Amino acid sequence: TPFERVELALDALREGRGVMVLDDNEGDMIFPAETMTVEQMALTIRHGSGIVCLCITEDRRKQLDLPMMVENNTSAYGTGFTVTIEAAEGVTTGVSAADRVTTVRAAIKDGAKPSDLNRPGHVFPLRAQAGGVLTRGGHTEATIDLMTLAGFKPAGVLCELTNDDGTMARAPECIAFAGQHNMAVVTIEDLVAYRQAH
Amino acid sequence: FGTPFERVELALDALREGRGVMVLDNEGDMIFPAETMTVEQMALTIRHGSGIVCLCITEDRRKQLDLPMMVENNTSAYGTGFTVTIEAAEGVTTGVSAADRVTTVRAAIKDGAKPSDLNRPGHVFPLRAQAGGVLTRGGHTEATIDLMTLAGFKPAGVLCELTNDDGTMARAPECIAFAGQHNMAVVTIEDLVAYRQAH
Image 1: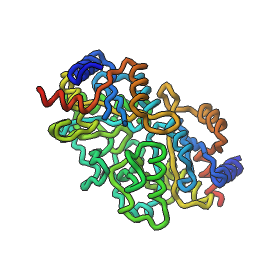
Image 2: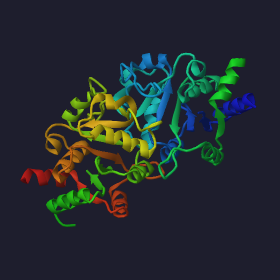
Image 3: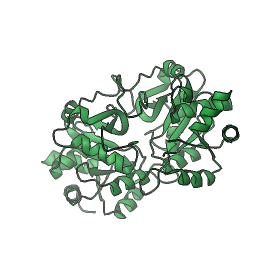
Image 4: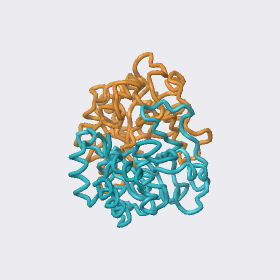
């Protein structure tokens, strides 16, 4: 059931596993920002678009002082990238799985201040829409709600799953793949239903 | 091994034959003529790259498209110089597929491209090359630009860092092994700097 699938995912997150979030033809591996490992970051760079985003809230955004990249968002989904980031220390080129994580941990770390970060960089922040999947049915909000439900900071890492031939992964592939990495599979509809109820 | 000048010219050939170049200075960047790059190639660079696939351009292509610099005060360790990211305003879907990235790229360079040809933000990341090239700034950005203009191309080229699968950045021997396995010409920014100084 929707509710079963949602709660089963919330578990996965707490056990520090990944979730494969789907909707409508693209699946996003996502992780708690707080728990994610280099090995996991490597995995997402290895099979992701390599465009690895850090979903955050408008308040974490204000806290770090990250302006929205564009004043007038014209992308097909109003995707909502802010200004990109690099950990102001602990990193080198900022591209290694090791470095991306480090950048990420600097962003979430309790009481992170803007000087903790360098702009631009190789981690790409996504501001979640206030209201979550009920305001906006996107992987961005989906990622945020799962984290806050799981009881985490409202910050989580995400990435599209890519076939090696370069095509975006379809559900059966996202599913095959989630299965092969102890990742809980869920859908934004499931999450919307779950939330509507509660 | 040969010479700086030999290596440089040998690369300029690779580019015209529509092959790739492995540019080193440590971190190696696969790069391609923006104009000639194929989805298969884009796939290859997403499959072994950081996945962060950039489109090096000139300040004039930047003005033409009306892309502001992402940050007003660049504080990155290398002043890397990203502008506002992009998506092809048509022909694409989610903009992430190798197919889609290319399409975004072709829209950007296409003769007489106007800003309305593009959507911001998106999944291709423009890099504005510093006026003066590798002689002003010794970066993969300018290295990419000079090679394209030397090869006789538009001053626009696609680039990406080579990543080991374990998630570590590729070192030279790897970049070399790899370039070798894809008919890619290997060159270094020093070689290019030397080449330019002469001419």
